[PDB]
Image (cartoon, rainbow over all chains, first blue to last red; front, side, top):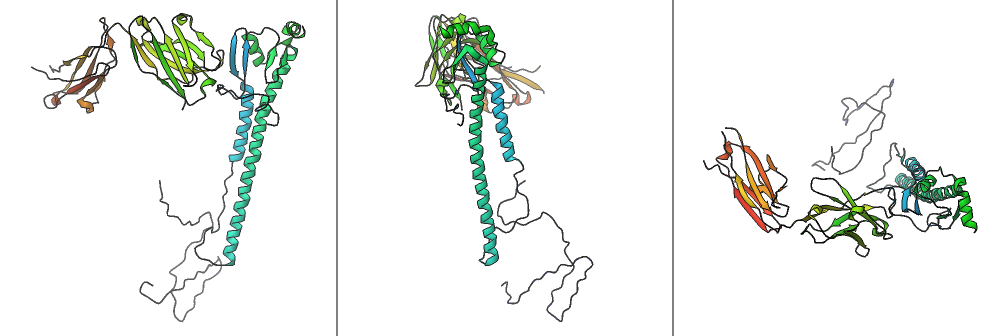
Length: 54
Length: 172
Length: 221
């Protein structure tokens, strides 16, 4: 696919306050540059082709 | 209806009464007329509005939703998701159908009721000076001019005044 | 949509008769009455009478008791108003309006027909003569127009440059001259400068006389 037979497996990890992230690898690591802030709330996702209007 | 007034002993409706739900038609020495009755029309309207608002109020469902559509076959978990949603939809469809039915039967019965109440009220006012013809019309056994008719429509009609004339006319 | 559709404009000479029609649609015709009301040009409303499409009852204003008869036809759902022995003061617009099925009822004239103009005149049909009103300025804003004189009966159409000219235009209501013929003027306000370049044509259309005329306006020094 896209000219390559080699791929990437993606994984996520949640770190709670007062806990540490630890990373250990001898090779084959695509590392994080940082994190995404997690929020709690009413947000969601929807699959639609409907145009958006004002 | 339950009271058998509307589509009951009342033959039909008056399409030419555009100013109310219920009313009086009269015939007397002066001519014939048609007037709405505000009090009962508003009774019925107020009830039906209250009902309507009770039905359309705060009925919106707001909480986070699972995935209701699926591209690839999976197995257990998805079979379960679908099952939950189908069950939900069926229960809600039933609730809706039933609601509409009960509500509507009631609306009809209640309007019937209002008609009948207005009728019994009128009769009780007329006391012994009139007879119930059976079609929702009263025969008034004394001369009643427009002022007097109005006095019946507005509730101030005093039967003792015409009692003698009327009784005399009924019983001989 | 509860529509009352009234017949065409009439033109009658004194002594004659007229019968006006009203075709009702959008409601049950025999559930109501119909009431006839006339309005003379630039005047108020005068009630002619009432009739029940329901029980056939009838109430006429004392004034029209003699000369008028109201009828209804249930199969066509149509009301008619007939006036006999016309005088010239009977000239007016006649309206037909929906009313309760019984006379002493509690509401009134809720739906109105478009009305039909009956003109009573001894004047025979004639087309308008059209003369220019020519502009002259004492470099400013100037006025010009058309005098449409001596026609009959009403109405008359007037436009400028076949419709291309609108803003600044005024067409006055017709006035009725002693002769029995109407007259009116149409007027436009335009820049004096465009006076010498652009052409101005007034198009007058009198339908009843089968007349269409076009005139133009120039100063003539």
